[PDB]
Every structure is written in C-alpha cells, then in structure tokens.
Length: 263
Ligand SMILES: CN1CCN(c2ccc(OCc3ccccc3)c(C(=O)Nc3cccnc3)c2)CC1
Ligand SMILES: [Cl-]
Ligand SMILES: [Cl-]
Image 1 (tube, helix red, strand yellow):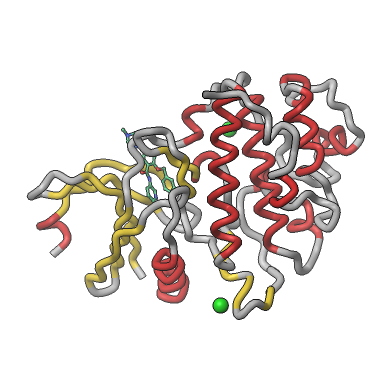
Image 2 (image 1 turned 180 degrees about the horizontal axis):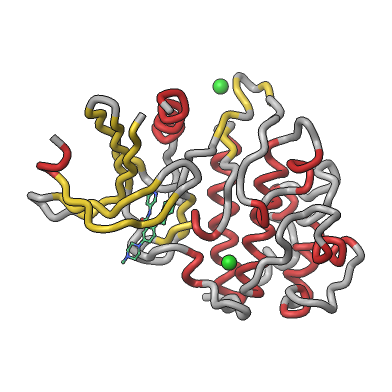
C-alpha cells in the first residue's frame, strides 16, 4: 500500500482541481511529485488520459498512477528548479534575456500541446516549472481538454482558468476557439516576466486597467517598464478580437522573439 512505499514530505501547491505533494520513496529516497485525489471519477479519468499522451521536453513527465479503492495517486517528475513564479521579482520581473528564453520554451510546449489537440486552459507562472538546467515545463492538466479530434476542431463553451490570465472572449462569448485563449495567457505570462506585475484583474470593461490598454496608454505601468520590442509583441498578443490575435506561427516571426540576446 502507498504509505508503505512513499512518504509525503510537504505540500508543493494546489492545481486547478487538487493538491500535489513532494513524495519520497521509503526505499530509494527518490523524490517525486504526487497528486492525490479521492474520487470526480469522470474528470480524474480524463486528466490521467491526457497525462498519458504527453511526451515533450517542455511538458512535465508523467510516471503513472495507482488506485487504492476510491483514491487515485498520480506520479510525476519533480521540478528541481521550482516554479517560474518564483523567478519573477515583484515589480521588476527578470532580465529580458531570461524572459525571452523562457518564452521560447513556453511556445515550444504550447505548440506541442496544440499539435496533439490539447488545450491547457490555465497557463500562468505557477504552472510553469523548471528542471535543474532551468528548462521550462508546462504542468497541471486538471483543466486540460481536447479541442481537436480526427482533424475536426471543437469550440469550447465552459469558462475556466484564472481571471487575470483569461482572454476577454472567454468572459463574453458563449463558445470560443481554444488556441487563441492559450496564446493570450502566454502574453500575460510574458508581461509578468518583464514587469513583475499583472496588468489587470480581468479583461473586462468594468476593469479600468484593461480599458487603459485598449486606449493604448502604454506610458502607464506595467507597459512603461517594458522595452519597445517586446511591447510590440505584446500589442499583437493582447488583441481583444481573437480572430485578429496573433497566432503562434506568427509569434515565431516577431522581431523581439528573434532578437539575439543571450548566449
Ligand atoms: C527544491 N524544491 C524543488 C521542488 N520545488 C517545487 C515547487 C513547486 C512545484 O509545483 C507547484 C505546483 C504546480 C502545479 C500544480 C501543483 C503545484 C514543484 C513541482 O515539482 N510540482 C509539480 C510537478 C509535476 C506535476 N505537477 C506539479 C516543485 C520547490 C523547490
Ligand atoms: Cl485524433
Ligand atoms: Cl506574478
């Protein structure tokens, strides 16, 4: 039984749907991340099925799972570097070359997900982890879902995620395309990395900071802290109409995205 093989040392944090712990094996001392859930059978079955699909250098590794009656045990690679959240200095961000590198890696992982028809739905720095060489890994598949199957796209029609990161259409439209929503959250992550603050509580008209952006007041914070090149990218990403929003193929052609900054 689980408790005979593993010791739960501490809480690593909460995901969208549960909580994950640092587990250390009682024989080998191998340290792993474990998500423990007392079975929704329907959602957890879904989370496990997506987890089994994943194989990419910028997505967390899934080791497997154990069911002990009603409780499911999900085992995954521990991120020795902790989270990206912890590299963002409040009100400062991080050095632009470090931000660009992490943004390159984030885009690599998101392209991989979208290419297998999965949308993450909750991209934010808490869910972006780092291995021992600071390679970024997209974690937490509790909200992830299928948006393309047999080459047919399905629109999403459920609101979820985290408000300061969600795209405006998720709050307004009854159904919407999955990919532009993930692209938007990437832009908020990039903003956070370069300014060390979030731009708004949510992207709604009742939020003044979001109105300010739409009116192009980039002389205000956080935008004033961001160099003109990454800012120009952020103007293409944080576009209100998802059909006019930049796609990942075009992000990959952006001037800042291609600027040499780092060894
Ligand atoms: C030295 N230590 C190393 C470990 N350090 C650390 C800190 C936070 C973490 O996750 C926050 C989290 C993010 C999403 C959901 C729940 C919790 C993880 C981690 O490895 N988590 C993980 C791994 C695989 C799958 N899911 C989560 C590791 C902190 C510094
Ligand atoms: Cl398919
Ligand atoms: Cl933050």
